[PDB]
Each structure stands twice: as structure tokens, then as C-alpha cells.
Amino acid sequence: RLSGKTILVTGAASGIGRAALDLFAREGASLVAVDREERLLAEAVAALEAEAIAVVADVSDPKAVEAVFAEALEEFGRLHGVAHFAGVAWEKVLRVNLTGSFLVARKAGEVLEEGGSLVLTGKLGVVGLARTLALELARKGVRVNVLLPGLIQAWEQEVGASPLGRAGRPEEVAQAALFLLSEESAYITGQALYVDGGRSIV
Amino acid sequence: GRLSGKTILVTGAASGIGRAALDLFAREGASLVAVDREERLLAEAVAALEAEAIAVVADVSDPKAVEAVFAEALEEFGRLHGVAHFAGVAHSALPLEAWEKVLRVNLTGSFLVARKAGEVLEEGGSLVLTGSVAGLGAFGLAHYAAGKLGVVGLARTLALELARKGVRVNVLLPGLIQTPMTAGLPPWAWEQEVGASPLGRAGRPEEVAQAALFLLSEESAYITGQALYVDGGRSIV
């Protein structure tokens, strides 16, 4: 489903980030795994049976983002997708995540080739950013979409997390991201897709 | 396959999108109950499949036809895992009066298939409803975006009610899709619609079928109440 493609993954040492790396590798993708946590990221990539590199970086820093995408292109020549999980990495932390989403999205926009796919995570905020870039980048054929996980994994307390009576699994968010990066979703851009068991149905 | 061991009921199974879904779901290991009003078109469509499949001629706006088609599906296959209701966009490519009755009748079919699917689908099952966002202006889009009424309202209301049983309900909103019935469109109208989609082309039947397969398979087990637009970005602005 991702054979022949290079995907850059931010927040790749995180629970969800890691489930994505594993699923994308089994589906034939080559990977640029990016995270600020050096120790866990080194472990995450070592375990893969795929063509992969690990890049230590702070994606809220404009110079480090510039460096990250240059290394990806130097190694694999061409970038086909970006799954931005650091968008889900309390007031100041949210502001810094928004700054990182902006910087990764704009750089992905310039660097991604025709038919490429940008998946962000969360008119205003990350959704407004995705829809604005979806319009700017449709000329290149680049698709821009957003994934909004709900509560992702005592067992009884989790029943109240969503109408479906459970919390989500990291692998389920990773599965939504695969759909959106793959050629199965070539005509889908500007979409906000909730992976939350119905939690946001209000 | 991605639907192995699953039985799927497909309405509008002789149409362009419906038929591309039959072929894709069959290639992915599903067994199928193919439902449509046009007999000769449905008989030919099913005969070409190399899957476990029955064909049933029925009008899904008729409450007794709906009860019968679901009863037949259970008698044949024992249990039902998914419903892809492509009759929800029947006669999409076609006078205000005639247009309203098409939408009204389609909404009737969506109600009846949704309720019956809700009754018979088992834990972890998936009902995929449909609506069309091709040719819509500012108010049409607001109606879909708000999610309170029409097909999106139905799906979101049912998602809440069926979540206890473990059943997911989602809706597919195709934009302009290149089916055979779209050939008889004036070129000026086709181009007006292509020009309204940021990606600058029509969708293919197969692409709407892939969105439905995602929604019916176990890869979307935590997703319910969602409106998924397959419109090349047409509805963004």
C-alpha cells in the first residue's frame, strides 16, 4: 500500500508515531523518523525491517525543520508523504505545537511532489491551516488532510471515553494515516477526520 | 483480503460506483448480497464476479422490499458485517420539481436501509451511507457542513444510538464522479464542476469504492459519525 514511497514522520518516538513507523514499514515505505527524544527514537528505528533514518530535531525551530527536510531529500531523493504526529506532542505547549504544525506544513508544501500527501494532527487552528494549504497546494496535486484522535490508550473508566465504550489504540490512528497517505485516497483533500469513537459528535 | 470472512450488502450495486464497489469488495474476500432495481443490469454485474454472491431485485424505498432483502441476506449467509448504501446517490446525474422528488425518495431509502441495517448488523459492524456534494452552492454546503439535517443528521443520530451495540455509522460524500450516466452531461456543466474542484479533475468510481472499503474494514474500527468528502476539495470553499 506504500511500496516505492518515502514518508517523513514527526513525533515518531511517541506511542502513535511508533505504531505508524511499524505499519508504514510493513506496507513497503521508506522512512525518515523525526523526534526531539534522541534515546527512544534510536530504539524505535533500530527495530524496523525497512529502509529508515532517524533525525533528532525540534520541529518548532525553523532552522531544524529546514535541516530535517534537506536530510530526507539527500537520503531518498524524493518525498511522497508527511505524517505530522508532533502536532499532538498546557497553554504554552499548545502554542508551540501550532508553531511546529505551521513550519512542518509549509516546508512539506514546497518539497512534496505531485500526488503527494500531507497529514497533520490536532477556519482557525490546525484545521484552518490544513484547509488553507489544501487550496494553495492543489495546483501541485498535493493533498492536505487532518487527523483528530480522541482519547488514545481502570478498564471501566475507559468505557466513558466515547460512545463506542472504549479508548482508541495508537495502531488505529496509524491506520487512518495510512489510508490518507496511500493512493486509495487520491481525491480527498481538506478533510478533518476524527478517530475518536464518536466523542466529538456534539 | 481486507474484507475476508465478511458479508457485505450493497445497494445501488448495478450503478457505476455500486458496481466498482462489488468488484473491489469481491477482490478483497467479501461475500456479497448485491441489490438494485434494474434486473438485467444487476444480473450481468453479479455474473461477472468470481465471489460468493447473490443478486436481489428490490426497490429500497419500499419498506417491505427492505425487510425481504435483509431476510434473504441472513438466510443465505447467517450473519451480516457491513452495508454500503450506494442507492443514496441513485440518479445523481439526473427541473427543480423532478430534482426534489429524487432527493426525497433517496432520503426515504436511506432511512429504511439505515434502520434495518441497525437492527441486523452485529457488534463491530459498519453501515456506510451516501450523499452527493456535486453541483452545490453556499447553502447546499452549509446544510452538509452543519451536520444537523438530511443524510449527515441521520448518520450522526444513528451513530449515537448504535454505538452501544458496537455498530459504526459514517457517510461518504462523493463530488463529481465519472460514471457512464455522466457522459450525457453538457460539456459546459462538466467543466463548471471540474473548475470548482481544487484538484482540477473528476473522481473515479473506484476511488469512492476505496473510501467505502476503508469505512467497512477493521482499519476504521474506532471511526463513527464522520462525513468523508471524496470531492477533490470542492466543499472547502
Image (spheres, coloured by chain):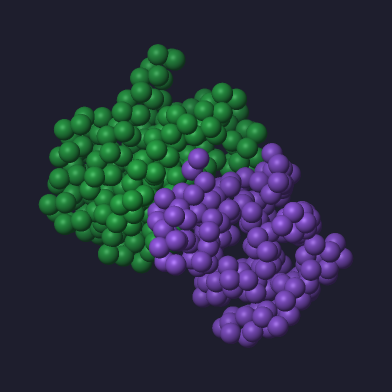
Chain colours: A purple, B green
What residue is drawn where x is 36% and y is 40%? Answer: B158
What residue is drawn where x is 65% and y is 60%? Answer: A88
Q: Is residue A121 above or below residue A191?
A: below
Question: In the image shown, does A79 or B202 lie closer to the viewer?
Answer: A79
Left or right of A190, for residue B33: left
Place of residue A31 in the rendered image (x, y in percent of width and height, measured from the top left): 65, 73
Left or right of B27, for residue A88: right
Place of residue A4 in the rendered image (x, y in percent of width and height, measured from the top left): 59, 70
Name the image quarter holding residue B145. Answer: top right
Place of residue A148 in the rendered image (x, y in percent of width and height, measured from the top left): 58, 53
Which residue sits furthest right?
A: A63
Left or right of A153, for residue A121: right
What residue is drawn where x is 71% and y is 46%? Answer: A125
Q: Does residue B34 appear in this view?
A: no
Which residue sits furthest left?
A: B75
Q: Quadrant of the N terminus of chain B?
A: bottom left
Question: In the image shown, does A133 or B114 lie closer to the viewer?
Answer: B114
Q: Is residue A19 above or below residue A90?
A: below
Q: Quadrant of the C terminus of chain B?
A: top right
